[PDB]
Length: 122
Length: 53
Image (cartoon, rainbow over all chains, first blue to last red; front, side):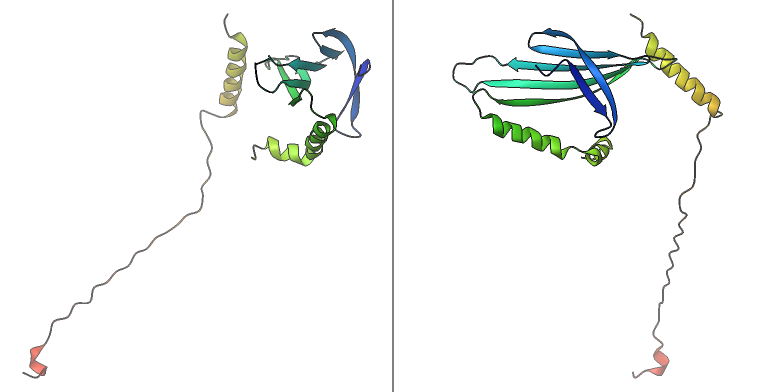
């Protein structure tokens, strides 16, 4: 599901909005694309289930990523930007608790925190 | 298999840097400190002509 068009409001709330569009779907994965004159935008969603091992807890993984590409101009070569999250939990777990953990992680992240983090401040 | 892009980028960077400067790096001075140690010795010798025997 998730709809056909995915919107990313670059710059947080109240920023510039872009509309990615669905282009393919394989292997429990979906990727959305948007061409640009000097750059390119893409988003992917992925789901996975780990191998079964005789007597151990079975786990599953969900991944979501945003990646940005800028075409090489003059001397500067190609380069990209990326930012993605991941969720790991037990197969039969309860949905509400892992959702609350994810919401907590989301809430902790905010402008000031990225500002400090990118300054190599641990 | 030649690494053309890296060579272009770095050669351009080094060329523009060299031409920006003149084969030199600038510098500035920090604070200036002065240390002045001073010592003296006071030695005595007993004069026996004004003392009890």
